[PDB]
Length: 146
Image (cartoon, rainbow, N blue to C red; front, side):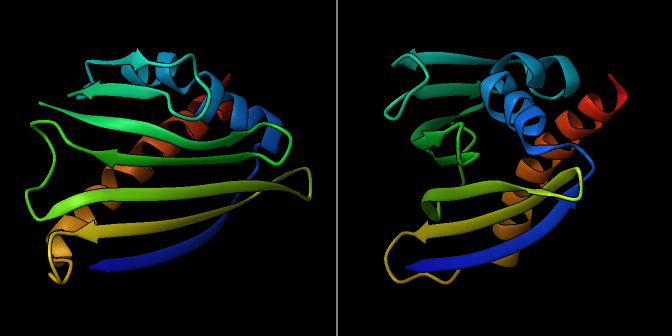
């Protein structure tokens, strides 16, 4: 089954700086800023679509679905590994920034793909949301501070 959520939010960080830190430099920044995340290793590709990353905390795999600096677009799918919930096939994120008042407007669309025709348990939704917002907010805070 397919379960989608959307969030729109804002940051004081302009989008090029925010995109650079969250997407371009994210692999290097995240292990440094989040104790629980040990490492992020590219196992396939060069950072374009198709790239696969192993995110160790147990671990999950992140696959780049789309990346565009010019439109501040980064779409990626989490699946697999020892850290991934058993009810989920994959979780696909679509993220886009746009300029707003010297900062950014942020749109995230998230699609949970469950096995079979299963609803999405609230606990799995919140786990994935908290981990992904946590990483984003940590990096954002870092950029604001430096």
